[PDB]
Image (tube, coloured by chain):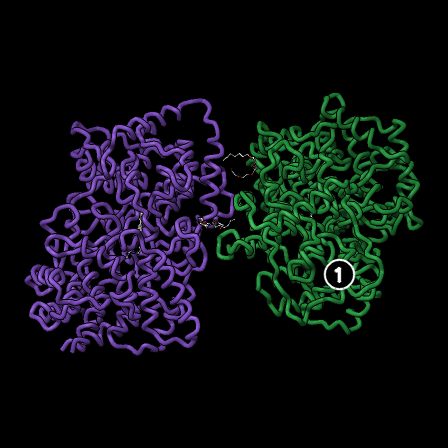
Chain colours: A green, B purple
Amino acid sequence: AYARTLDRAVEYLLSCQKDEGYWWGPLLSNVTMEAEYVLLCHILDRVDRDRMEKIRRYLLHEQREDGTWALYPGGPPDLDTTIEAYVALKYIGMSRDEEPMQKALRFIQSQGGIESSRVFTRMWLALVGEYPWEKVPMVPPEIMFLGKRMPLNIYEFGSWARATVVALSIVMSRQPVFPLPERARVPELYETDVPPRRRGAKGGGGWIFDALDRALHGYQKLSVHPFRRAAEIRALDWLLERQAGDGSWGGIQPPWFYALIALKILDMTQHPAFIKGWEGLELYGVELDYGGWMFQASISPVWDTGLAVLALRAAGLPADHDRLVKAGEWLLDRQITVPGDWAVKRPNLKPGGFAFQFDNVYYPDVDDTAVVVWALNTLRLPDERRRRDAMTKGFRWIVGMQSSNGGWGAYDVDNTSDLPNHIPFCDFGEVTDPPSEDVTAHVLECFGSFGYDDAWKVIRRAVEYLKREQKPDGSWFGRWGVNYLYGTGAVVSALKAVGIDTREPYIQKALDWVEQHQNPDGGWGEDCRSYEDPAYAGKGASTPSQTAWALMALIAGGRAESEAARRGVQYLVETQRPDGGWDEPYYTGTGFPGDFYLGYTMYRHVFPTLALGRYKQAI
Amino acid sequence: AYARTLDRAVEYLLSCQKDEGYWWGPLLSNVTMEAEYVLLCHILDRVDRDRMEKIRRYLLHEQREDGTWALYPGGPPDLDTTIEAYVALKYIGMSRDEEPMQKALRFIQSQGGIESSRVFTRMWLALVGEYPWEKVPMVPPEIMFLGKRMPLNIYEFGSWARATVVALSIVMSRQPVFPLPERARVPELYETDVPPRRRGAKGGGGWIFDALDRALHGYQKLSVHPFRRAAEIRALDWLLERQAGDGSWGGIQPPWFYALIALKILDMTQHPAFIKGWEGLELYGVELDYGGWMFQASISPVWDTGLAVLALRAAGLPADHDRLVKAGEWLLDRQITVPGDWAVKRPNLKPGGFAFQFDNVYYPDVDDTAVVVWALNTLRLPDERRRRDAMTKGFRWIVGMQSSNGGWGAYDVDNTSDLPNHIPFCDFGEVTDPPSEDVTAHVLECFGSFGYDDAWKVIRRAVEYLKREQKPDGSWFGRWGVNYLYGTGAVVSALKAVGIDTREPYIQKALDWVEQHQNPDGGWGEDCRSYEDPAYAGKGASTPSQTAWALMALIAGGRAESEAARRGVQYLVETQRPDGGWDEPYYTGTGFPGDFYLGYTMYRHVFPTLALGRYKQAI
Ligand SMILES: C=CCN(C)C/C=C/COc1ccc2c(-c3ccc(Br)cc3)coc2c1
Ligand SMILES: C=CCN(C)C/C=C/COc1ccc2c(-c3ccc(Br)cc3)coc2c1
Ligand SMILES: CCCCCCCCOCCOCCOCCOCCO
Ligand SMILES: CCCCCCCCOCCOCCOCCOCCO
């Protein structure tokens, strides 16, 4: 039956593999990437008329009937995203009249205008002079003086927030303004009567931080700021030391852009670091066949490759298939062997992790490292020496990364401070990197492959963590993947792999929850709204990936030979395309719950293949 | 008569001009450049068999009958240079037997062996483990803590020494060893009976520094060096901030190589600065037609271009010649507009200088700046706006650069400390950058072109400086050009340009000295030995450049219509080649008096043309 579905999915995957031996699907997000890019180009005075064009098609192409842009496809209109896209277009050439500009503007006004947008959005506008800097939450260079163990030192922030904070302190230190031509000024963003509905800090704003900010804005007005000169150079040096190989900073859009702006501010346009950071941008860009151009928030080569392998294996290909060897070899050359920001909390821990992107040595993450190591553990490569060795380093590193609650974060250990969540500046996404169910699950499943079972204390401490984090209805939150279907799929699969008994009560209570959300069409789907409103948990249009996730949960829990089970397999078999792939018009990836969603292009092909590969196993 | 010589020389220079509009002659030095390169490659584990070959041909080709290499062509065998070349060859493949290896080896031994070589040479050997680190003068990272105004803070060193000191403190901090294969070990460098004739610090070694070093090597042995971690990072950041656009450091061989080694030491071979620093090297390399390959100690594009223009103008071409405009435009794009290390002593001084090489913004020098500005002053470019403006900036920068004694240094103001000259480490070349007669002269002649005569206090203070520095016999030392013929030529030409009276006693006493050293063959020549033994001052085989220098001195002093005068013109007119150029098998350039000499490839063509252009003027 499905066997053909598999043979067809397999050959399709293999056809997507690049020459070097890896897989690399693009990463989808929202238009703030390209919108901010346009603005960046203006700040750096490096505008390419042809590029703007391609960007205009894209922005428009992405706008909806109502004239707005959302975070995820088929989602509620987003203010910030729409404001930024609006300004972007007006600068590229559009007139506030044109149909699109019209629809958007009205939606923006019906929301309280610019005064209701996240800090970033107001900050960008502040940068081109369309918003007073005084009203933007202040982050001082002096934050660079806080010690390793102090309230709000930069290492109390998540890796992704950290670099941004550093780069920004330099920018906010100078509060520079790069005026836009009159043709693009957007005063109309204020022209509204609706009351400005301000978004506050993630965890609520104590009156302390409120005061402190006003404080800082006042100090900012003084004529002399002693040691500021030094605080800046401190930040700069911090940035210069960490620049990634591709010229980015962390391989993520934000800090990269801010860092570049900051160098511009410091008259360092013709310094090696600036030049490289600038040229690097192109690698993250993508030519859209309909004429547009988009910029990736980040890139997932390693990750894509890692899952690719595992899927193709669980599928059927030989642990030494010459095409998988190409990948295995490639992966080995990726292993990070030098200290990263994580060493600040683990000085005696030997380097051995992996990054998400191509060349980002200071920020390996547990998730990638776990999947990669495990994927390798399933291959037989020529140099069994290096494979054995690689694995062991990565493994040890993963173990040394385990946090205090027996769980695993993504980039740091016990990056669980609560302080950062209350600053006025932090009103978007996550700011800290605490342990999560999905990463912890992936780790356990990694160790699982090696055989380490529930006996080992490390594994237990972790299971205890998961057991305590389970939800009332028996599901598990999905931190980096939409959502409960993603998490529950992870945990169960993991627990199964570490020897735990699939028959336990809590396990059964999870599998039940799964069968319970199967859509009429036989598959499963969970919409990104499930982060904002619970009624959506496990509810949504069926997708190949999410279906594949629920299947893995079922296959692991023994219910492989179920109705719901065989039912979901049908869905995949039917919905598959002639070429072997699958379609998926919905995002199944999560950047920040409720704030930033991602579309992992390869998910639709790899997870269905891995789920099917594992079903063919249960028989 | 000579008119043809000029026409011929002119069209020749014009044929040497690159497309972009500049001139760029190679820079000759000695084999330690290529020898150190070989070693560098070994340290970085990046050896290209093919390149090694090209370097062997070169090394050999440069060796002399006696089996030694000298600093300047036709000079006494140099120990350090020969030791380094020896080791280089042995590593590339030579056997201690072969004729070349034998002759060299014996010369080395007849000198006390390795124990008689400069610090650098022993250090390089220490790096590959052929010499104990304990016996190498120690320079600690902690030097990074001395304040702006303190004994031996890094800004008390000359720009070229500074960067090296920083990069090295990191290296000496770790005292790393990169072993050579047994095949190349050079124990035989010790096998000698002759007493080791040790070279001491430039200005003498007080017993203090002697003790201090011993102190440091002791502290080096401790198990804990508090804050060293930070001293290193201070150095690292200092380097990271100053890397040049081409990836070099200062556009000079030394620090660039050391910095690269230092990054390697810190596991930063995957960092942008290193990759760029590494790829940058190729630009300084040069394919030799006989199969060899050489590496330039530095590059003189700006300088060459600057003089090229002036010569072609004084010769005759129109101030708006389309071919000179190409140059003028090019030069404008070169002006440095950001703070350099010089700002540490001139914070309120506006940037406006120029560098020697292509892209080296933190180290513009007075010499280049003066020649460039002045050369522009002689042109008529399309955008008279930028020309007017640029000049002004440069001018101001030059003025603000004048030191305490009315003289001008090269890179810094009053970089005249005496402390650095006594450290055990500093046994090679110059370590400080004090004012010199030639630079000061070039500056005066620059201003001179504008009009600013002796009235202006600036000019006077300077003339006073020169007047006091003149030698007993009426000559002027040549700091960056071999030597008295170079300096005296500069000064006199300058003084003439600033309105002074060529008839004065001291002026006449100079011109006389000139006429007095004219060689029988009608030309002038001064050998590089004139830095070690006075009997050589103004003595040596005639060269096109030095002849052209003495001519400018004579033409300026009114004695243009002299015997010696017309006599020297003959020399040039005759010795000139059929193509238009001139030959010059001798170095006329000076890096460090008595320690490092340079061959300016373009000198032989430009100065003769400029001297001839100025003779055609006196009629
Ligand atoms: C899929 C598995 C998740 N696991 C953990 C691997 C790591 C993935 C990379 O995680 C991120 C995490 C954050 C980001 C951002 C981003 C976007 C906007 C802001 Br504001 C800040 C960061 C852009 O790309 C990102 C990628
Ligand atoms: C011709 C005019 C001189 N004027 C002033 C312009 C500046 C020229 C650059 O001066 C230098 C000055 C020093 C160096 C070194 C060098 C070589 C060995 C060591 Br050790 C240290 C530096 C290599 O190249 C150099 C070039
Ligand atoms: C000069 C110290 C070299 C020793 C490196 C250990 C650094 C420990 O990391 C602590 C914080 O820095 C995070 C890592 O990325 C650092 C890059 O800087 C490179 C070498 O200092
Ligand atoms: C963050 C301060 C930036 C202002 C620096 C100017 C300081 C005065 O110059 C001191 C000497 O250092 C030379 C500066 O240029 C080198 C690179 O350092 C980068 C920031 O300017």
**In this orientation, does residue A19 appear?**
no
Q: Is residue A266 left or right of residue A121?
A: left
Indicate the quadrant containing the C terminus of chain B: top left, top right, bottom left or bottom right: bottom left
Q: Identify which residue is drawn at 43% across, 75% down.
A: B383
User: What percent of the width, then of the height, locates residue A338?
Assistant: 55, 36
**In this orientation, does residue B205 appear?**
yes
In the displayed structure, B535 sits above or below B507; it is above
Location of residue A379 by image quarter: top right
* Tag 1 residue: A83
Q: Is residue B271 left or right of residue B598?
A: right
In the foreground, A22 or B1: B1
In the foreground, B265 or A381: B265
Q: Identify which residue is drawn at 90% across, 32% down.
A: A509
Location of residue A442 by image quarter: top right
Q: Identify which residue is drawn at 51% across, 48% down.
A: B272
Location of residue B375 by image quarter: bottom left
User: What percent of the width, then of the height, locates residue A1?
Assistant: 85, 47
User: What percent of the width, then of the height, locates residue B400?
Assistant: 36, 57
Label 1 packing within 10 angstroms: few (<14), some (14-19), many (20+): many
Q: Identify which residue is drawn at 40% across, 61% down.
A: B352
In the foreground, B242 or B403: B403
